Each structure stands twice: as structure tokens, then as C-alpha cells.
Length: 147
Length: 134
Ligand SMILES: C[C@@H]1O[C@@H]1P(=O)(O)O
Ligand SMILES: C[C@@H]1O[C@@H]1P(=O)(O)O
Ligand SMILES: [Zn+2]
Ligand SMILES: [Zn+2]
Image (tube, rainbow over all chains, first blue to last red):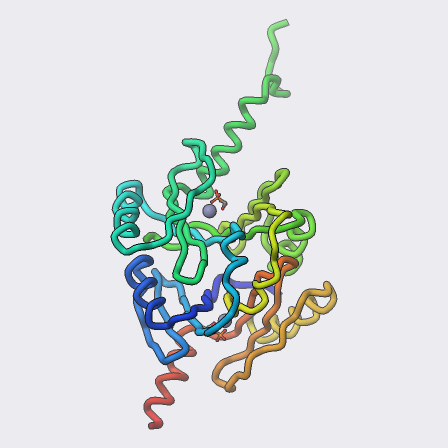
């Protein structure tokens, strides 16, 4: 039957020791336990796992726009971009934006998993597209016309 | 960080993936477009963006996946949903009983998902109980 909500995310990593420092520093995840092949994090109530897969091809992932986004404020976005620069993170060129899309930062973990810091919400994105829609509406049936 | 904003999956065929996300993950469609679709799944903003031209073969070797919470009988029923919809079911990893029950599968483009019947706390305890034992 029904799915109740998100349970956990698992990331395949090639280096447990370096991936831990990435997820702690860049994503501010709180390490809960670690072995030699696993690490569990709490990220604001979200269970995140790192599972080691030592030698797999990780080149095609760079070509896929599949990504995970986290919410930050505008001042936080600018703090984080500097943090990502001083911590040597691969920062992706994002797509062209509209100002109504709200600002974003795209980047990857040491194994190519794409992440995003976003200032907007689903609200805005739907409020965006709906305003665009209203722009193309000239006759509102039900309205009373003069003549 | 304020938590998860949204998750985006690159798909090759929009209508084919939209059905998957509708029928398998039970996500509620909000809006479609030429190369996009937005859902709401248990309060999560799920987005699909289409990219037809890219190679999607190496994604098979990575254990990277996203898990959703289900009850044990939801899992039983969901297993037949997968099979009936010819969903790419992966055989599970070796599990202790305290691992709780799971079912792993992929969407048409190789993104891996899991229906899981446990919690992190369930798992931490199974790990902690191991320490207590020793
Ligand atoms: C919970 C971490 O994702 C791994 P599992 O699903 O193999 O337990
Ligand atoms: C919101 C859907 O993920 C895409 P975007 O990040 O390019 O806007
Ligand atoms: Zn995004
Ligand atoms: Zn899992």
C-alpha cells in the first residue's frame, strides 16, 4: 500500500574516510556511527548512509542531471559557496536561470553525486509558473463584460 | 541547511517515467511540460527533467539509492505491484533478521529505490545490541 515518507539515502563512495569529511564539512551532516565500509549520518532528521564500493566506473554519472537539493537562505548560499571554494569542491556550472527560479549552487561529492543549495521552494516554482500562466490569460470566463 | 528542498531525476522518456513515479512510488503529479514534471510525494518535491541523449549503463554498478518507509504488509503487496508492472527488481543484499525487510528496484533509467520496513533507530540498536553482546 502506501509509502509513509523518506526513509534514508545511500551513497556509494570509493573512499569512506574522505567521504565522511565531505558530508560533515560541506553538508553539515552529523556522523552517528562508522565501520570500514559504512557510515551513518543525521542531516536535520534525514538518515544518510555511505556504503563503500571500491572500484566501480564513476564517469557516466557526470553526464546525468540527477541531483539532490537542500534549502538555504540567501546569505547562507553566499557563505557556502566560499566554503565550497576553500574546501576544493567541484562546483558545477548550473543551467541558465530566471530570477524567479531563485538562486542555486550546484556541486558534487568526491564520487560525482550532484548536490544543490537552493533558496527557493516548490511554492515559488509553482507560483512562478502560475504567474507566467496568468500573463497569457486575457478573458476570465465568469467576469462581467461592459457591452 | 534547512533540510531537503527537492530531488531531481534525469529521465529519457517523460511519459514512461511519469507512470513509474505515479504507479510505483505513488507520487502525486502537479505539473507536466515538454521536458519536465513536478510531483509531491509524502511532502517531498520530486522533479523529473528529460535528457534523452546520455549514456545510462554504469549506474548499475553503484549501490546509490533512496529508500521509502513501508509497513511489512505494504511490502508484501508492493512486491506484486512491482512484478505486475514489470519493474526492474534487484535481488536483495544479505540481511540479518534485525536488518528488517526491504525490496530493491529501479526506475526505467536505472535510479535505484528501496521499500524499507525499519528505522535508523532500529538499525542503530541492532548495531548497539551487537556491542552490548561483546
Ligand atoms: C541503510 C543503508 O542503505 C544501506 P542498506 O539499505 O543496505 O541497509
Ligand atoms: C527543480 C528541478 O530540479 C530541477 P532545477 O534544479 O534545474 O530547477
Ligand atoms: Zn534542483
Ligand atoms: Zn538502503
